[PDB]
Image (tube, rainbow, N blue to C red; front, side):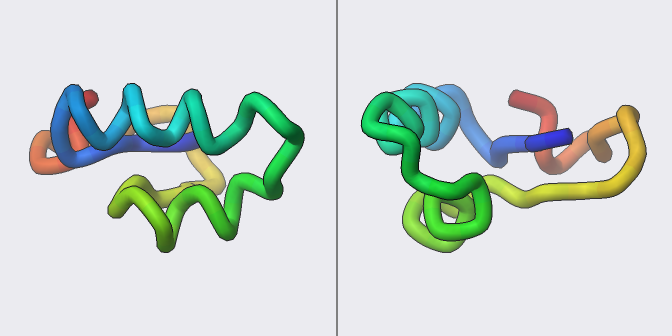
Length: 46
């Protein structure tokens, strides 16, 4: 599950994924994170 720290970070993550870029690279590029569960924390609310 991916969790992003702001709306702009999520929008950038979604563009990063368009060509098929791995989630892990789009995470470090944008500041979003990947967690094994389904429940994003309050500081990664987007």
